[PDB]
Image (cartoon, rainbow, N blue to C red; front, side, top):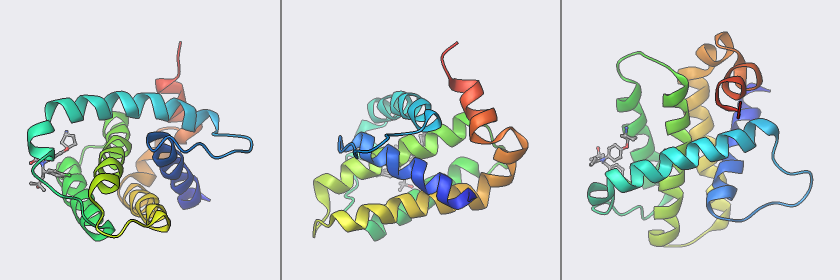
Length: 148
Ligand SMILES: *CCC(=O)N(c1ccc(O[C@@H]2CC[C@@H](N)C2)cc1)[C@@H](CC(C)(C)O)c1ccc(Cl)cc1
């Protein structure tokens, strides 16, 4: 269930940014902690990198996937993995969602689940083993970022 858990975190973050809460039992405790930390990092990246983010047009899910993979390959190229870098992946997906909502040439809600897929694929394939060895999401991420 490793991929599915990360896909659900990425989808919950996307629904948070788009302000489209899905009814039912709601997000898990990991998801709730992740949403505040990643949103804080997202607003900081948006502010600092506004000029260069504004020069790019996210016109399709293919462009979002390509930009996500190029930016995240560079973010992790030195071989270091830490929780802050993992929170930045979610923050970056939130930026791409916002730009896609503004500039997607043929708007399609069913294409938003493609973003949660390519975020989960990157996390699983590049950081999954480190995540497990550092406590997973409940004994690693939550313990580190939950309120004291
Ligand atoms: C001003 C930087 C820039 O041109 N790009 C960019 C690089 C990295 C980045 O975010 C990561 C995560 C937070 C930071 N630690 C760095 C955001 C923007 C562009 C990269 C290109 C030129 C494509 O390689 C860029 C611009 C706009 C978008 Cl939507 C994506 C990437």
